[PDB]
Image (cartoon, helix red, strand yellow):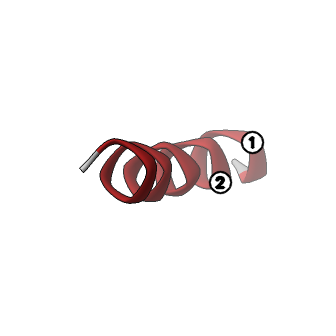
Amino acid sequence: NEVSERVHVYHILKHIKDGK
């Protein structure tokens, strides 16, 4: 499913790069 796969990959990069 296109919605399920893309939301998962966007949250991993947003939390590590912006948060640290």
Q: Secondary structure at mark 1?
A: helix
Q: Residue 20, percent across and down?
A: 24, 50
Question: Which residue sits at x=57%, y=52%?
Answer: 10
The three-letter amino acid code for the residue at tag 2 is Arg
- Residue 18 image offset from top left, x and y in percent: 44, 49
Up the image or down, 20 lies above or below 19; here it is below
- The picture quadrant where one finds residue 13 is bottom left
Q: Dot 1, crowdedness within 10 Å: few (<14), some or many (≥20)?
A: few
* Residue that numbered label 2 is attached to: 6
Relative height, residue 1 to residue 17 (above, below): above
Where residue 9 sits: x, y (%)?
A: 50, 57
Task: State the residue in front, 18 or 13.
Answer: 18
Q: Is residue 8 left or right of residue 1?
A: left
Q: How many numbered circles are shown?
A: 2
Circle 2 — which element? helix
Query: What residue is shown at x 40% (from left), y 59% (from top)?
Result: 17
Query: 8 and 20: which one is in front?
Result: 20
- Is 6 left or right of 8, judged from the image as shown? right
Label pair 1/2, CB-CB below 8 angstroms: yes
Q: Which residue is mark 1?
A: 3
* Residue drawn where x is 69% and y is 48% of the image: 1
Which residue of the protein is positioned furthest toward the right in this rendering?
2
Q: Label 2 crowding class (10 Å Cα cut-off): few <14, some 14-19, many 20+?
A: few
- Report which quarter residue 4 is drawn in: top right
**Location of residue 3 in the rendering, given as x and y in whole percent from the top left corner:** 74, 42
Q: Is residue 10 left or right of residue 8?
A: right
Identify the amino acid type marked 1.
Val
